Image 1: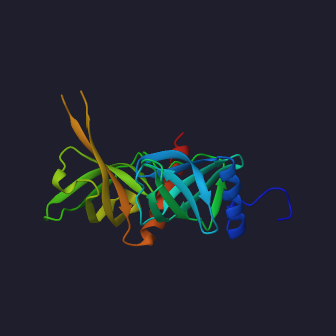
Image 2: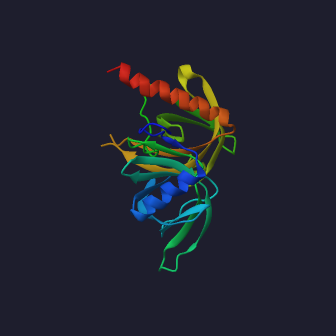
Image 3: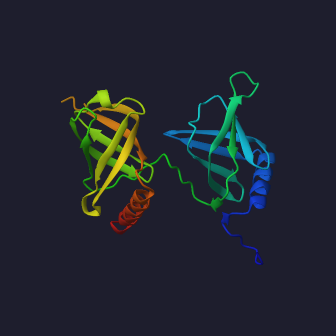
Length: 231
């Protein structure tokens, strides 16, 4: 760098640790995202390879968790794989060691992955349950990580927690279709009152191929933009 203004994307292994070490010492709040849950805590340690955080909550392993560092300079976005966990020697506290991010991204606005765009299109999801039975869902809202499906007559047997919905077809109207695996994250029954009941089904996208992801991100962009031309 030669000017004052900084680049927002950090790929330097040395600046990264430097960034994490400073924020640790400032007790900079770190936000941890997973499913519809978010928790606020602090960095409990930083070595050359991994950063630490402690919490009683149980964070899912085997896939990079979304993070948000609330530093004075702005929100520092990054993903990090869970690389180790065990009791923190503090009552019920779990110790989480995440591999240091290899790319930070400093932004100014809050980007909460838990929130989904509520389109205005008629989107559907069709497919067959493992017992051959057919299912049809309305796609209420959507995001590059998941969606909310809705139906008044669901087959709950195939809709338990972390249940699977493989090769499901995202009927996305004009944008075409997209065959993908969905894993049920949680199910609730909304009741209007006539005592209509709707089963909202929250699903995490499990891609058969990353190409699907690049498309669902563009489609999303065309909607967020479409939400601004209408107003």
